[PDB]
Image (spheres, rainbow, N blue to C red):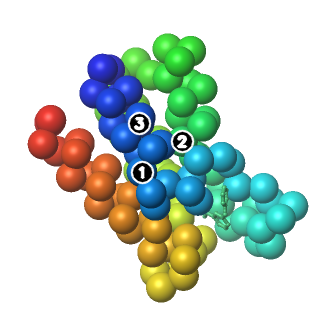
Amino acid sequence: LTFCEIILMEMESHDAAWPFLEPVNPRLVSGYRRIIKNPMDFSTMRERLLRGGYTSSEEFAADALLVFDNCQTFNEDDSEVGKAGHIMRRFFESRWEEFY
Ligand SMILES: CC(=O)c1cccc(Oc2ncccn2)c1
C-alpha cells in the first residue's frame, strides 16, 4: 500500500491529471449520469486510501482502471479529456508494472 500512495501522489500531481482530480459533476456534464454506472476519480481514491479502505494493491488498481475505463467510455479518444486520460492510463500502467 506504500506504492499505492506513491503512484496516487504522482498521478494527482501529473500534468494530464486535471480531468480526474475531482468527481465529474453530472449537472455540468450532459449525459454522464446515464452512461457511467460506477464513476471514479482520484479524490475519491484519495479519500478511501486515507481512510484505509483498500485491502490490497488489487482493489486500488481496480478503481484506478475504472477511472480510465469510464474516461474512454464517455470521452472520444481525440477529445481533450480523452487525450489526457490515455496519458494517465499509460502512466499508471507503466509505473504499476515496474513495481509489480
Ligand atoms: C473524467 C471525465 O470523463 C470528464 C468528462 C467531462 C468533463 C470532465 O471535466 C472535469 N471533470 C472533473 C474535474 C475536472 N474536469 C471530465
Where does residue 45 sit, x and y in percent of width and height?
A: 53, 34
Q: CA distance from mark 2 to mark 3?
A: 7 Å
Q: Quadrant of residue 46?
A: top right
Q: Quadrant of residue 25?
A: bottom right
Tag 1 residue? 14
**Which class describes the residues within 10 Å of circle 2: few (<14), some (14-19), or many (20+)?**
many
Query: Residue at image x 70%, y 55%?
Result: 24
Please tell me which of labels 2 and 3 falls first in the chain. 3
Query: Residue at image x 39%, y 58%?
Result: 88
Which residue type carries mark 2?
Answer: Phe
Which residue type carries mark 3?
Answer: Leu
Residue contact at pointers 2 and 3, CB within 8 angstroms? yes
Where does residue 44 sit, x and y in percent of width and height?
A: 61, 35
Left or right? Give the position of 29 relative to 39: right
Q: Nearer the viewer, residue 7 or 33?
A: 7
Please tell me which of labels 3 and 1 falls first in the chain. 3
Q: Residue furthest top?
A: 52
The answer to whether the beta carbon of the residue marked 1 is less than 8 Å from any atom of ligand 1 is: no
Tag 2 residue? 42
Tag 3 residue? 8
What secondary structure is marked by label 3? helix
